[PDB]
Amino acid sequence: IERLAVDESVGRAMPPQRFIEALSDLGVPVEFAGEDEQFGPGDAVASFGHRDAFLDADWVHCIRAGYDEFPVGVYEEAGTYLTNSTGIHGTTVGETVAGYMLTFARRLHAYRDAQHDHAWDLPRYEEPFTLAGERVCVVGLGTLGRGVVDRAAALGMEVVGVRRSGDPVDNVSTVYTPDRLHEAIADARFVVLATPLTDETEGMVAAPEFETMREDASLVNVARGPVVVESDLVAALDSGDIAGAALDVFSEEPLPEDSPLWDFEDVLITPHVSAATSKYHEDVAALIRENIEKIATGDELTNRVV
Amino acid sequence: IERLAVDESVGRAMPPQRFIEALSDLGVPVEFAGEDEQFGPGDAVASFGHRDAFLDADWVHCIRAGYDEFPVGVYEEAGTYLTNSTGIHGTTVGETVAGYMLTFARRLHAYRDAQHDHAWDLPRYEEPFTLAGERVCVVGLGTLGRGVVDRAAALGMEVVGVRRSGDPVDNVSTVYTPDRLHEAIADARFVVLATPLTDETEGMVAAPEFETMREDASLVNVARGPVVVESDLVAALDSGDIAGAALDVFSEEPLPEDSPLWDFEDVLITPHVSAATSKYHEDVAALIRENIEKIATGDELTNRVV
Ligand SMILES: NC(=O)c1ccc[n+]([C@@H]2O[C@H](COP(=O)([O-])OP(=O)(O)OC[C@H]3O[C@@H](n4cnc5c(N)ncnc54)[C@H](O)[C@@H]3O)[C@@H](O)[C@H]2O)c1
Ligand SMILES: NC(=O)c1ccc[n+]([C@@H]2O[C@H](COP(=O)([O-])OP(=O)(O)OC[C@H]3O[C@@H](n4cnc5c(N)ncnc54)[C@H](O)[C@@H]3O)[C@@H](O)[C@H]2O)c1
Ligand SMILES: [Mg+2]
Ligand SMILES: [Mg+2]
Ligand SMILES: [Mg+2]
Ligand SMILES: [Mg+2]
Ligand SMILES: [Mg+2]
Ligand SMILES: [Mg+2]
Ligand SMILES: [Mg+2]
Ligand SMILES: [Mg+2]
Ligand SMILES: [Mg+2]
Ligand SMILES: [Mg+2]
Ligand SMILES: [Mg+2]
Ligand SMILES: [Mg+2]
Ligand SMILES: [Mg+2]
Image (tube, rainbow over all chains, first blue to last red; front, side, top):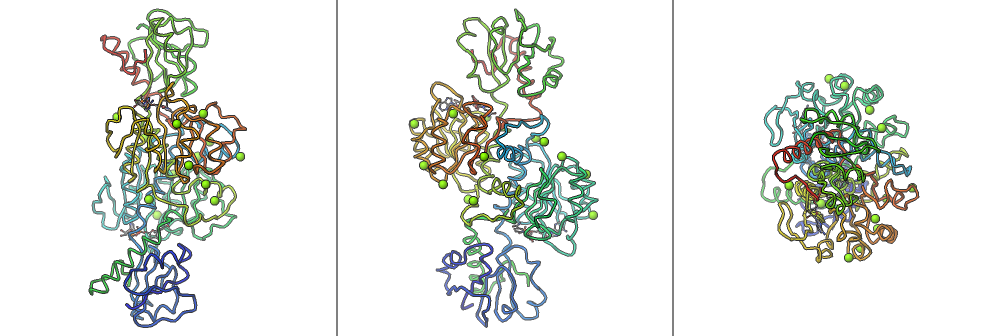
């Protein structure tokens, strides 16, 4: 690799100059790249989204964990390496999800609504509870899922989860394979989605899962919107099949103003910012540095998609 | 002790019939007591606040941790024992405070405000941060303080604290005496107040403390309102001497509708519910069972004030 181009699209997550400056001692020059740039041998590119121009480069680094919007087959045939940013979002997302769960347990969102009205409104006696002793089911036990798990466990929660192998995971009391999803979620106060969007995960959580879930339970989606059937979620909320939801991701983003999801008291909408951090530039830069080292020494790239 | 009277004032915290039912099989009858009840030898009374009528009873158990609204000198003179409920609020308050801090770090309150407007409003890049690596100073290292410390530590925060003895406390890196309060707070992102209201603590946090505090810092008050000079807090928030506050307790409660505190975006107001729990009746009943035994056997009462 002779050059790192920083595609302007990284601006969707972080100021590009902040990222460029973070990489000033990388060992190769780092340059801002506009949307109408050509690439060639020796070029690495960091980007938010895909461009066909990137196929001429040696290596593209996607600055997101999710790569479901990249044409993986087309990279494979063009001989371009593709990496993602999995592994850097566990603290941010884990903290946000702890925040969602504590908001629901302690009723912080309801108090915030009352604050706007200058209203000293006491909760119903049965409403406030502690996370300590409550059960969370974490679906997907990778970086995001483990970040959630570790914080839930530290807060005294009973933690169960779902992963491909069904094999044990640190801080998870019971791990289920994906075919036992209904057993995994049935007794949970919170169900947290942390899987990639795949053929297999699309529409995973729909009306039947909402039926299975406790009426006092809340869904947390920090994965991708289409893991949930969004219309079924609306119907479940309306019907009281579940109590509420904390949603960072949606089938359409920005979430249209006409979505019924905005108006539910016990829904939290966040605008795809559960992983937001003022140091994102540093966190992504560390990945770039790691792979530049691996390229230099001829080892296998970290987070290689194709 | 021949009778446990449950004062109607317990309804300020929990439904009285739920508490009475939780006190079944004490070995003595449990009776509801209205505001004109007379007391006498053999009576224990569980109450939220003080009545002079209680000075004819053997023992009053205050159902709150804080007892600053009880005329302690007068109980001594009358020979009536007084106990409080310290020791049972660490999980509830600890969780609420973790929730406040996560709310600020992850910008959840801003997203909630936007949700009312169906607005997909992105934070400025610098706004979202992680609690991991940030410093919290906890002032008062008792049940509440330690419940805060333990959760802060578990979330990866740097934790310092203030106590009189300056003796070390588990999960606190550095303990300061109160004459070093300004050293303790100077570098903290969050300053949490968890002391009783006493002659010593009244007005502890005022203009000089707000000057000392970082401009990006937030005050959390879960103690009593008058530990803070409220007018100085308002001035500090107006001037930007600190960034914000999470406030559960106030110099006047309910907080008057025309308090300036309601209107600050980076203030969270909660209506003295940081310790709220749907099992409060069980938690207090356990303490009463404990102290009935202590009286029966002639041992020193738990949480004896006078
Ligand atoms: N909201 C955000 O800002 C944000 C940030 C980062 C990631 N994400 C989303 O979260 C996803 C996961 O990110 P990550 O960094 O944890 O990825 P990861 O690869 O570390 O973990 C994903 C885990 O899900 C597992 N998995 C796959 N299919 C599954 C199934 N059917 N059932 C249960 N588990 C399954 C994988 O084996 C893996 O262990 C990303 O693909 C992305 O869509 C969202
Ligand atoms: N917001 C709520 O719902 C809620 C709930 C419970 C308690 N409280 C308030 O919090 C206070 C503390 O409750 P707790 O259960 O932690 O009490 P506690 O007795 O367990 O702890 C109080 C701590 O403050 C320390 N302290 C006393 N005076 C001090 C001083 N001058 N400087 C520094 N430290 C001092 C004590 O030594 C003790 O460690 C109560 O008195 C009450 O006012 C509020
Ligand atoms: Mg309600
Ligand atoms: Mg609990
Ligand atoms: Mg299904
Ligand atoms: Mg259901
Ligand atoms: Mg409901
Ligand atoms: Mg703003
Ligand atoms: Mg941090
Ligand atoms: Mg203790
Ligand atoms: Mg002072
Ligand atoms: Mg200041
Ligand atoms: Mg005050
Ligand atoms: Mg300011
Ligand atoms: Mg207002």
